[PDB]
Image: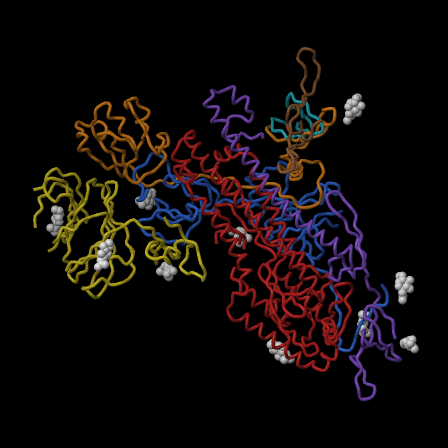
């Protein structure tokens, strides 16, 4: 949601409620991959995404985790800055969305608009309730929620602008009459219970 | 004082036509077989939309075709002190519309309809039909009316046009409201100055951005919202597994697809019946305005009326017509 | 040939005249307004389409025969509490050997009719394989409740 | 050789008796 | 089919036919229309493009990766213009809001759905803004108009008589002078 | 009444005979729905026509009051020309008005003046205009040429 | 008929031709002065002999 609160870290076990928007900023590459799991022990299944300097490798097995893999199911190997990722899990599929933006300041999240393109849809059917970032210089975590958006597509296929339909009364009015400009008057938008 | 005021009236609205089989079924033969069970629905809807479309031409004709004989615009536009150059067409200009008409046509700002502008077509089967009388043929009528009012006065309403000087027309029209002739003749230059100044005020009031044509834009906006609802209803599900006939036809057997086709047919027939009913209700609202505009054109442009507040506020002297997109503007 | 006629009946019930609606534009007008005399004017008669002249089929460059043998005829299936998902990609799948053969007791397809499976073209196919008790086969269906 | 059959070959379509009507039918006709 | 297609059955690919009304099957997506080259640009994860009414208006060729626009084959209404049964059995036909070069060749190739066994397109084919008019002879003179087609074009039955189509005239022209010391007065009634 | 509306038959006797009762209710209910909608359409279009007939009747009542029972000064209300009187005649589902009007004809051209000055003072006409026969000036009314 | 309803039938035994007509139906309207005035009413059977 627009203008929501995001928690910043400058390695806790951050919960994974419905999805995460994970934004990492770094002058030199520090944040390398994540680990997703239910109990983060030998008892339950867990998946690791990590890139070494040549490759990106995803492996889903029973791991020993502390900061020997058995019963493996899924394996994949493929061959300043601000990196934005969206992770969401549904129907046994993990969706990853990735975008890149060049910025200058490290301390704070800059304000702006940036769209994210699909990268991975992984067919691994586990509950993911927690995650830990893997490190070798700040990262921010926000949580997704079910909302209705309005997206504007220009003459090409790019999403230039959007409105959240639950931020303000005015945003609900914009979603109700299908525009970004509103004339003077009184308009009936919705019903209250 | 001499006051010139504006009345803005709608006369016609946009014609439209719908292909019933192309909207409901498209190119499917299986859908076209099941549509025959519901009867003669498409012929009725086509007949109703055809009737509304043929009504709009009569709405325009009864208002603007008030002159049997067409008068050429006089080469001099300064009659007895009164400056008529801003309501008559310019002798040297590519467009035939006058100045105020050119302001009004840019005042009202008029996709996916499917009209020929290059003939283009859309998948949904809707079309917008062109009017019988173009913009130049309407501007010719209003130019003839303004030329006749300046030259012959009230006389051409009731017979053959009889010439008369404009100052004597104004003396007669002053006799109409109870004031004598010597009020006009002794003070003619002042009245001419007030006439020219009021025309110049009208020009700047139009040149400044305004909502004065908010009645003619509402005719534009109500048609556009009528069609976007009709198009968007093609995306609704109506209970089937999908809202597209090609995927239902492609992923399912014929006997299983019969039910899913019937759901879409039942929904789309209702979505089209609603549109035709609302257009029939709205055309009766347009017709009342067209009849009132014809009455104003007869009783206030080709004559002088004694009815209170029928033509402006004050004591009526003269009136001029101008053509605006989908309507008329009386000065 | 199968055509549409309009026939005129007199007071004694004998046919005296008829028009053939497929002969002329004028005969179609007479069939549309149901009369043998027409006034002056313009009458909207019908709708016209243009029939297609060709056919185009475009499927990608895929040549490998599809391994349905390994999925169905395999030595070991896992138990139901730990099932396995296998991804099938980049193959030409015949699909006819599934419903032509009498091998399978229950072949129940949701959202797709089996006969149309040979025409459609997909992105990936996922096969989930397991072993259940004989009455637990009915619980493999959308929106159904049980222990399995 | 070939000739033309002008307004010939119409027949009574069915069992029904009708009078003073214009009746439209679809059937195999010449 | 959210990704490029990989798993599907045996069907033989054919050459694509452009600017011609065909039945098409693109990756299991079936339709009827004409196919043209397109200026739209696709990002690599997209395979087809969609309209407001959930119609598919663009597609990517699986072999050559060329973006193609899909348009409907020509359709519309057919109107018949007659002088009257008492006058003559000649009629003219209006095909509403289509290009004349499409209908004029579709009649010759016998690929039009209202199939009339005895019908000749003939020499007179006229393109109006209302559509394609067949069987009416254009004339240069202007009259008051009887049968209104539209956009200022009307037809009538005029002289060996035949159907003619012309631009309507608004009224009989007349000029009255303006003199500042001159009046006209009726002398009878 | 002839349409199936998706049922098996138009006539209800065949539907009742050929099927059992529970299926017959389902088949009859679709015909019932279709005929209800076919009747509601007719009622709505008749209401919209009755509005138009009311508008014409109100205008005819106004013309009967103003044109027949009195003389009307409104331009083109009671016919072209200058109104003198009007006569009503009955017709099936309507009325026919015969308006009698005065039409000027045979115009002549004269020279005209706004006012004349006799001895240091200006004279304006009470009713009518000043005209010039060529020999001497005269005063007339505008609609007829009777020089005074 | 013109509305495609059966109006005439030939008798199978005698070969006699006979007409079917619908037996009478219609509307029933009640004419009353008012409950406060009187409890008598008149009845109009519309379009019937
Ligand atoms: C930030 O937003 C979250 C959203 O649920 C809310 O719980 C939290 O209290 C907010 N923090 C502050 C300081 O307002
Ligand atoms: C990255 O990890 C993969 C997976 O073990 C390995 O095959 C590859 O050699 C590694 N690359 C390095 C260490 O540069
Ligand atoms: C669409 O892309 C082209 C190609 O760079 C670009 O020139 C154009 O400005 C883009 N459209 C918009 C609305 O920016
Ligand atoms: C009449 O008005 C026009 C437009 O305002 C102006 O250009 C012209 O000079 C005027 N004629 C006169 C003052 O004689
Ligand atoms: C008709 O088609 C030709 C050939 O494509 C084209 O050049 C012309 O502009 C078209 N005309 C209309 C009115 O569509
Ligand atoms: C019907 O038959 C009677 C009996 O011969 C005959 O008088 C009449 O003319 C016939 N009707 C017509 C239309 O010829
Ligand atoms: C598919 O095969 C055809 C046939 O040789 C070839 O022209 C085309 O380039 C191939 N496309 C791809 C993507 O391999
Ligand atoms: C007016 O017309 C009538 C008939 O046309 C004629 O008898 C009469 O003499 C005319 N009046 C004059 C003044 O010419
Ligand atoms: C007025 O006089 C002019 C010039 O002689 C003439 O052309 C014109 O016809 C006259 N007016 C009328 C109404 O006859
Ligand atoms: C005009 O009328 C007067 C009075 O009847 C008459 O004396 C005079 O001769 C007339 N003029 C002409 C040119 O006949």
Nearer to me, B157 or A26: B157
Supply the letter of whichever chain is orange: C
Q: Residue at x 7, y 50 (%)?
A: A67
User: Chain E is shown in which shade?
Assistant: blue
Q: Toward which corner of the image does residue F117 lie, by quadrant?
A: bottom right
Residue nearest the viewer, comparing G13 with C53: G13
Position of the N terminus of chain B by quadrant: bottom right
Residue A138 coordinates in the image, percent (x, y): 16, 59
Where residue E92 appears, x then y in whole percent?
Answer: 66, 45
Between residues C29 and G15, which one lies in front from this camera angle?
Answer: G15
- Residue ranking furthest to the top: G13
Q: Which chain is red?
A: B
Which chain can be seen in brown?
A: G
Residue B148 sits above or below residue C74 on the image: below
Quadrant in the rendering for residue F92: top right
**Is residue A84 visible to the viewer in this orientation of the structure?**
no
- Image quadrant of ligand 3 equals bottom left
User: In this image, A65 relative to E153: left or right?
Assistant: left
Q: Is residue B100 above or below residue E38?
A: below
- Where residue A35 appears, x then y in whole percent? 15, 48
| Quarter of the image where one finds residue F73 | bottom right
Relative to residue F8, is residue C37 drawn left or right? right
The x, y position of residue E44, in whole percent, is: 31, 50
Shown in purple, the chain is: F
**Chain A drawn in what color?**
yellow
**Chain rendered cyan:** D
């Amino acid at each position: 949601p627009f203008y929501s609160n995001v928690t910043g870290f400058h390695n806790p076990v951050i919960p994974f409620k419905d999805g995460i928007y994970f934004a990492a900023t770094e002058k030199s590459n520090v944040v390398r991959g994540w680990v997703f799991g239910s109990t983060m022990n030998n008892k339950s299944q867990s998946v690791i995404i990590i890139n070494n300097s040549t490759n990106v490798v995803i492996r889903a097995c029973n791991f020993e985790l502390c900061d020997n893999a058995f019963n493996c199911t899924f394996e994949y190997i493929s061959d300043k800055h601000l990196r934005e990722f969206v992770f969401k899990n549904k129907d046994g599929f993990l969706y990853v969305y990735k975008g890149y933006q060049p910025i200058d300041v490290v301390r704070d999240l800059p304000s702006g608009f940036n769209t994210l393109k699909p990268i991975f849809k992984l067919p691994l059917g586990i509950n993911i309730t927690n995650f830990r970032a893997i490190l070798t210089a700040a990262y921010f975590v926000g949580y997704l929620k079910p909302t209705t958006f309005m997206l504007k597509y220009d003459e090409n296929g790019t999403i230039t602008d959007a409105v959240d339909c639950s931020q303000n009364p005015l945003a609900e009015l914009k979603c109700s009459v299908k525009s970004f400009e509103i004339d003077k008057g009184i308009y009936q938008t919705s019903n209250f219970r | 004082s001499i006051s010139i005021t504006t009345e803005v009236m709608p006369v016609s609205m946009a014609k439209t036509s719908v292909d019933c089989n192309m909207y409901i079924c498209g190119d499917s033969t299986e859908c076209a077989n099941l549509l025959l069970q519901y009867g003669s629905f498409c012929t009725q809807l086509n007949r109703a939309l055809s009737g509304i479309a043929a009504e709009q031409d009569r709405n325009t004709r009864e208002v603007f075709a008030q002159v049997k004989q067409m008068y050429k615009t006089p080469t001099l536009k300064y009659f007895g002190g009164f400056n008529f150059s801003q309501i008559l067409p310019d002798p040297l200009k590519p467009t035939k519309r006058s100045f105020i008409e050119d302001l009004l046509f840019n005042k009202v700002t008029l996709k996916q309809y499917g009209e020929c502008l290059i003939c283009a077509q859309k998948f949904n089967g809707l079309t917008v039909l062109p009017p019988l009388l173009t913009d130049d043929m309407i501007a010719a009528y209003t130019a003839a009316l303004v030329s006749g009012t300046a030259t012959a006065g009230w006389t051409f309403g009731a017979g053959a046009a009889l010439q008369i000087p404009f100052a004597m027309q104004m003396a007669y029209r002053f006799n109409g409201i109870g004031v004598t002739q010597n009020v006009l003749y002794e003070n003619q230059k002042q009245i001419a100055n007030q006439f020219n100044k009021a025309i110049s005020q009208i020009q700047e009031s139009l040149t400044t951005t305004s909502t004065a044509l908010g009645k003619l834009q509402d005719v534009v906006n109500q048609n556009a919202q009528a069609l976007n609802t009709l198009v968007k209803q093609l995306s609704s599900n109506f209970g089937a597994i999908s809202s597209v006939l090609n995927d239902i036809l492609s992923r399912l057997d014929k006997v299983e697809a019969e039910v899913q086709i019937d759901r879409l047919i039942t929904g789309r027939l209702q979505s089209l019946q609603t549109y035709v009913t609302q257009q029939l209700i709205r055309a009766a609202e347009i017709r009342a305005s067209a009849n009132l505009a014809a009455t104003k054109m007869s009783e206030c442009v080709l004559g002088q009326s004694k009815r209170v507040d029928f033509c402006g506020k004050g004591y009526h002297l003269m009136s001029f017509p101008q053509a605006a997109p989908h309507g008329v503007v009386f000065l | 040939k199968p055509t549409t006629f309009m026939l005129k009946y007199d007071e004694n019930g004998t046919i005296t005249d008829a028009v053939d609606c497929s002969q002329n534009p004028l005969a179609e007008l007479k069939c549309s307004v149901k009369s043998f005399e027409i006034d002056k004017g313009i009458y909207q008669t019908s709708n016209f389409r243009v029939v297609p002249s060709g056919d185009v089929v475009r499927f990608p460059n895929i040549t490998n025969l599809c391994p349905f043998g390994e999925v169905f005829n395999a030595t070991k299936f896992p138990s139901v509490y730990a099932w396995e998902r296998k991804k099938i990609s980049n193959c030409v799948a015949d699909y006819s050997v599934l419903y032509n053969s009498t091998f399978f007791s229950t072949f129940k397809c949701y959202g797709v009719s089996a006969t149309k499976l040979n025409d459609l073209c997909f992105s990936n196919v996922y096969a989930d394989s397991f072993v259940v008790k004989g009455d637990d086969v009915r619980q493999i269906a959308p929106g159904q409740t049980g222990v399995i | 050789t070939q000739h033309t059959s002008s307004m010939r070959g119409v027949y009574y379509p069915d069992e029904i008796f009708r009078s003073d009507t214009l009746y439209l039918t679809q059937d195999l006709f010449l | 089919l959210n990704a490029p297609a990989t798993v599907c059955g045996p069907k033989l690919s054919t050459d694509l036919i452009k600017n011609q009304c065909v039945n098409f099957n693109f990756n299991g997506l079936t339709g009827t229309g004409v196919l043209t080259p397109s200026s739209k640009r696709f990002q690599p994860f997209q395979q087809f493009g969609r309209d407001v009414s959930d119609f598919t208006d663009s597609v990517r060729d699986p072999k050559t990766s060329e973006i193609l626009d899909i348009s409907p084959c020509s359709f519309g209404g057919v109107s018949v213009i007659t002088p009257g049964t008492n006058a003559s059995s000649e009629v003219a036909v209006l095909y509403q809001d289509v290009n004349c070069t499409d209908v004029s060749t579709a009649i010759h190739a016998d690929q039009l759905t209202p199939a009339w066994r005895i019908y000749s397109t003939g020499n007179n084919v006229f393109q109006t803004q209302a559509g394609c008019l067949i069987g009416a002879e254009h004339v240069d003179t202007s009259y008051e108009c009887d049968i209104p087609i539209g956009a200022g074009i009307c037809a009538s039955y005029h002289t060996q008589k035949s159907i003619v189509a012309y631009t309507m005239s608004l009224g009989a022209d007349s000029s009255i002078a303006y003199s500042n010391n001159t009046i006209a007065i009726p002398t009878n009634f | 009444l002839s349409s199936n509306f998706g049922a098996i038959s138009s006539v209800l006797n065949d539907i009742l005979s050929r099927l059992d009762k529970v299926e017959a209710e389902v088949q009859i209910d679709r015909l019932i729905t279709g005929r209800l909608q076919s009747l509601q359409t007719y009622v709505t279009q008749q209401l919209i026509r009755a509005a138009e007939i009311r508008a014409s009747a109100n205008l005819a009542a106004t013309k009967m009051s103003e044109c027949v029972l009195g003389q009307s000064k409104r331009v083109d209300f009671c016919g072209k020309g200058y109104h003198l009187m009007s006569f009503p005649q009955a017709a099936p589902h309507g009325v026919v008005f015969l308006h009698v009007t005065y039409v000027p004809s045979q115009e002549r051209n004269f020279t005209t003046a706004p006012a004349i000055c006799h001895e240091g003072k200006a004279y304006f006409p009470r009713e009518g205009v000043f005209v010039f026969n060529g020999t001497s000036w005269f005063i007339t009314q505008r609609n007829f040429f009777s020089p005074q």
